[PDB]
Image (cartoon, rainbow, N blue to C red):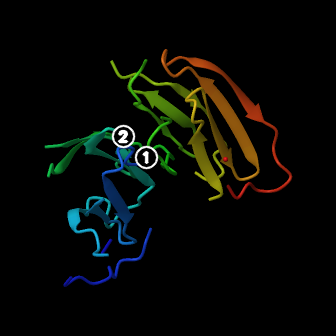
Amino acid sequence: LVPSIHSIRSPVKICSDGTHVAASYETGNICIWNLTPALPAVLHIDDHVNKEITGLDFFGARHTALIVSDRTGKVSLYNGYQLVYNSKKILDVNSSKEKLIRSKLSPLKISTNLLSVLTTTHFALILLSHVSLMFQETVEPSVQVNSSISWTQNCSRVAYSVNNKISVISISSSDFNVQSASHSPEFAESILSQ
């Protein structure tokens, strides 16, 4: 993934269908390759360039739509119109001492659209599948970066560990209802990372 081709000078920074490859350029750019000749480029994205890139991942079967997370753009809506991905901002949460740490494709009947926003002042999750909020818990405002968040493959619970602290909230997949939550005790050492 790069025959008159050359390696990409940009350093490396969730297509469930397995038909494309996404490369995260270190300059806030994203490259798409059609997935021993290299895979030809399919698209280039520079919206996240000159800005923080919290995370990104393909929208499952909706390969045309691309989910991209930024500490400034925050909630958006991207659709693939060889479909060019055009995105319109939905809501920005860069202010009020809130910054998006990371976000990618959710766990994978209810469509997978519950997206979590890891904000330092208060973490939350908006359950888009009108669009509502899955939950909102006031996180420690010290950050406002040993923070990470993931969702179980069963889509029944999602954990999040920040510094020497952790908390797991269990939410139903098909019903899209938060079953319960529990904040784990503070660890003796900072959590570097399932």
- Can you tell which quarter of the image residue 27 is in? bottom left
Q: Earlier in the sequence, mark 1 or mark 2?
A: 2
Examine the rendering and report whether any part of residue 71 can be seen: no
| Direction front: furthest residue | 36
Q: Residues within 10 Å of mark 2 (few under 14, many from 20)?
A: some
Q: Is residue 175 above or below residue 92?
A: above
Residue 101 lies left or right of residue 74; in this view the side is right
According to the picture, the residue beneath numbered tag 2 turns out to be 60
Q: Amino acid at mark 1?
A: Ser
Secondary structure of residue under mark 2:
loop
Q: Nearer the viewer, mark 1 or mark 2?
A: 2
Tell me the kind of residue under disc 2.
Gly
The residue where tag 1 is placed is: 95
- Residue 4: % across, % down: 19, 84
Q: Using residue 120 as the reference point, say whether residue 21 is left or right of it.
A: left
| Proximity of marks 1 and 2: CB atoms separated by less than 8 Å | no
80 sits to left or right of 26: left
